[PDB]
Image: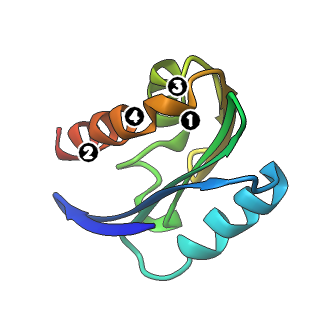
Amino acid sequence: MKEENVGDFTLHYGVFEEVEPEELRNLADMLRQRTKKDVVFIASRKGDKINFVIGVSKEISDKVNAKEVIREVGKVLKGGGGGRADLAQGGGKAPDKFPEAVKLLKEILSG
């Protein structure tokens, strides 16, 4: 996975093959504990399905609401999502659309 600063945030993102959803969630959780400005968008492709997670540093939960953002990237990935402002997760039907979801998230983070 990659790291890129976007606006006042640090975005960590990547899509993995064959990672279990609960493992993916735990990884995202760990990665957003790093700093106070982390946004983590990671996904796991299992064949023609994709599971994805958004985790943010707790300090920026109001700024980047994972509840809202998960649904926005979820739409691109032909899926849904839900959770809390600091950590949310979903499943979708369009694994090949991850790059497009990442582009959207960067646009969201920049405003």
Percent position of residue 85, x then y: 57, 45
Q: Residues within 10 Å of mark 4 (few under 14, many from 20)?
A: some
- Going from N to C along the chain, the mark reached first, 1 or 3, is 1
Q: Residues within 10 Å of mark 1 (few under 14, many from 20)?
A: many
Q: What separation in Å lies between label 2 and label 4 (alpha carbons)?
A: 9 Å
Residue 77 badge: 3
Percent position of residue 66, x then y: 52, 43
- Going from N to C along the chain, the mark reached first, 2 or 4, is 4
Q: Residue at x 79, y 49 (%)?
A: 21
In the rendered image, which quarter contains the C terminus?
top left
Q: What separation in Å lies between label 3 and label 4 (alpha carbons)?
A: 7 Å
Spot the residue most to the bottom: 34
Identify the residue position indicated by label 4 in the image. Answer: 101
The residue tagged with tag 1: helix, strand or loop? helix
- Going from N to C along the chain, the mark reached first, 4 or 1, is 1
Percent position of residue 26, x then y: 75, 65
Q: Is residue 84 above or below residue 35?
A: above
Label 4 close to label 1 by CB (< 8 Å): no
Q: What separation in Å lies between label 3 and label 2 (alpha carbons)?
A: 15 Å
Label 2 close to label 1 by CB (< 8 Å): no
The residue tagged with tag 3: helix, strand or loop? loop
In depth, the one of 98 and 54 nearer the eye is: 98
